[PDB]
Length: 48
DNA sequence: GTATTCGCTCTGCTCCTTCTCCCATCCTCTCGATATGAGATCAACTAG
Image (cartoon, rainbow, N blue to C red; front, top):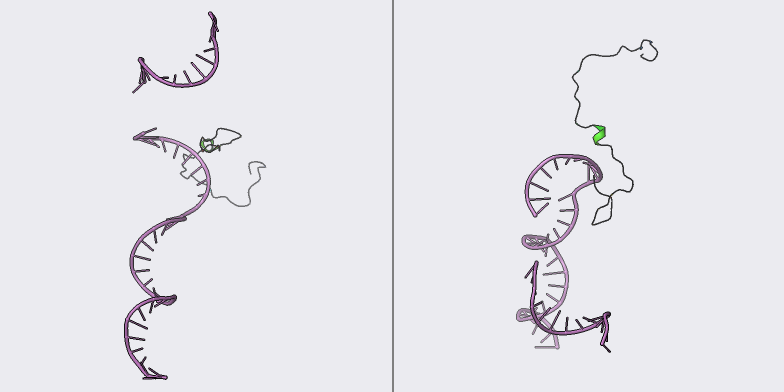
């Protein structure tokens, strides 16, 4: 255990595995709104 | 004078045809397409 240095009772399965970083980053997805722009036809919040 | 039909109508019954409707939610991104003045009328001035 990294926090206490005690051995973990279960022996953990560990080794090299090929991982991929995918295009989907949270910083390109996070979004918030509070009284922003509105659509012309119906005066409702925009899309996107 | 009643059989007996019998023509004609009145639904009504299946069926085929038409037609109209519907087909999860939410989110991100990219990419392509999408005239000008003259004359007349009228109304406000803008003064005489």
